[PDB]
Image 1 (cartoon, rainbow, N blue to C red):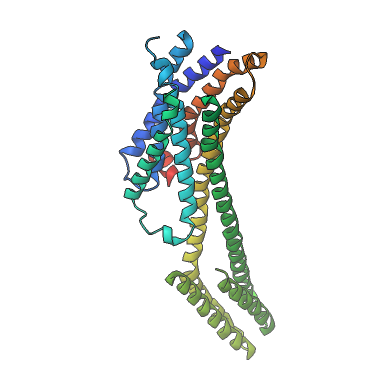
Image 2 (cartoon, helix red, strand yellow):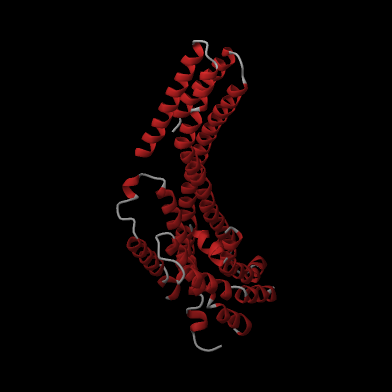
Length: 360
C-alpha cells in the first residue's frame, strides 16, 4: 500500500503550503499582536515547518538518496511538530479555562510579553524532548515516554478544562433563560393591562408583574449596582400603580403602568443585550478550539496505536508484516493532520472576517 501513502502525502503537500502561507501572512502583518492570536500564529508556524519537510520523506520512501540525513533528522521533524502542537494546544486550553477562573491569575501579568515568553518556553520544552529521537532496549522506553507525555496527560488536561468550561456555560445559559422568561411575563402583562378595563384585572396583572420583577432582580461591581437600582425603581413604579388601582382609579393606573416602559428601556435593555452578546461569542470561540483538539487527537491516534502494537508484538510474525506495511499509511495520515488543520479555521470562521475574527 505504498502508493496510497505516496498519493496522500503528495496531496497533503499540494494543499498544505498555500493554506499555511496564506494564514500565516494574513495573521502576521495585518492586525496587532495580542495574547490570543500569538498562540495560533505559533501553531501555524510549527505546522508550516512540519509541512516543509514532506518531499524529503517522499524521496526516502521512493528511493530508500545521499548522506545519513535521510534516516537522521527528517524522521525527527514529525516528533518535534507533534510535541510542539500538543503543548501549544494544552496551553491554549489552560488559558481559555483561566479566563473564567479566579481574577488573581487574570490581571496579574496578562500581557503580550508574558505570551511570547511562555511561547518561547513551550518551544524550548518541545525542543528538549527532541534530542532522544535524533541521537541513538531504547525502543522499550522512548515509545512509552512519547505516548505518555504527548498523548495521555495533555489530553486529560484538555478534557478536564473543557468539561469545566462547558459545565459553566451550561449554567449561565439557564440563568439567562430565567431572566428572559421574567422579561416575557413582564412585557405580556404590561401589554394586557393597557387593554383591560375594570380595576380588578389591573390589580391581577400588577401582582404578576411585581412577582416577576422581584424574581428578575433576584437573578444574577457598579454594573450589578446599576442593574439592581433599575429594578428597585421598577418595583417602586409598580407600587405607585398598585396604590392608584386600589383606590378605584383605572386611567391613572394605566398611565402609571405606561411610565414603566421608559425606565425598562433606559435601564435593563443594555444589560440584556450585553448578556446575549457575551454568551453567543464565547460559544464560537470555544467551538473552534474543541473542534481543533478533536481533529488533532483523531488524526494522531492511529500512530500511537500502531506504535503500541509494534512494541507489544514479537517480530518474525506475519502480523508484523501487516503492521509495517500499514505504518506508511499511519505516518502519512499523521502528517496530513498539518494540512487538515488550517481548513477548519475557514470552515468554523472578506479575508479578515473569515480568518482574523476566527481567533477572537
